[PDB]
Length: 370
Image (tube, rainbow, N blue to C red; front, top):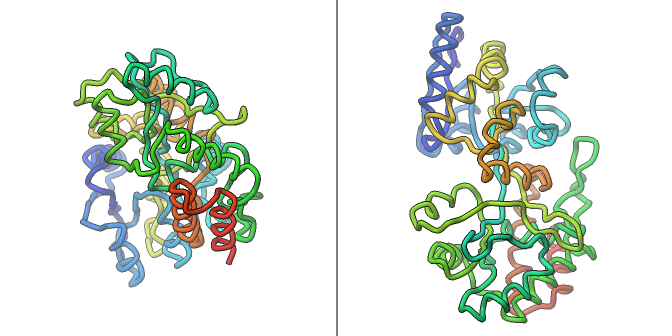
């Protein structure tokens, strides 16, 4: 069993744990309650094992894409933030922490791909995908390419595919319809066709992966790339004069990247559910709380409006949130793994020529709906 009278928190060591501990001292100072933070290896794997025997931490911090499986095994307690507290965070973040209609976690930070460009090569990045082909011809006359990004993982191409209508699973009334998949509709085919055309016209090469794109970009060979916050440090050291901005639109509609939400859940077996709620709502999810974490280590875009507005003075963090607000929340249901294999394959086959956009997406849809 979990000891009553105190709080034990688990969070990955790459996050600001000393910060959370700092909020913990504040909490103890205030209430006299002890708060201890631990960061075990493979904690996201350990949690379901120890929580299943009625043990583990009171609170667990991790990307929401793992909370669906946790809730599915009843490993998380239903949280009870009232309407006023909920209105303190961007509305879209709450959709990432709902399990079959029930809120099962507090969103903390938001992640999503943005458009990264070389300010020297491109003082004014393109507002649309449509204008990239001609921009590439212009730049190639100077021995540079317009854009390069990972074409081997679905996360990087989906923003364009979803712009005109593609989606993973229909989400309405707080829930997903596992039977409504939009992988082979006109919107998706339009986006993939445009991606394929770029390749066909030699603006991009179907073989470009993550390593190749970063190399080209950090080396000043290509004017733009698509990647998340986790890639910035590597660019900082390349000394490239880079900027981060909203993704290009397609057919007048915003690209829609998948959004990841760092969340804090309460162990279903925790006898300290009330202390956890007090800690999370009134200590961590405040400007002072988040300020303590961020300082120890960067949080990036946060879900708390008031503090997000402060961090947003950094155009890169503001861009992450803009792209996230226009993005598609990453579904946490089990079928999402089928979508990721099916779509990775379709994109690679359409890109290589092994399949037409029509056939590749037709087979993916069928695969995901089975």
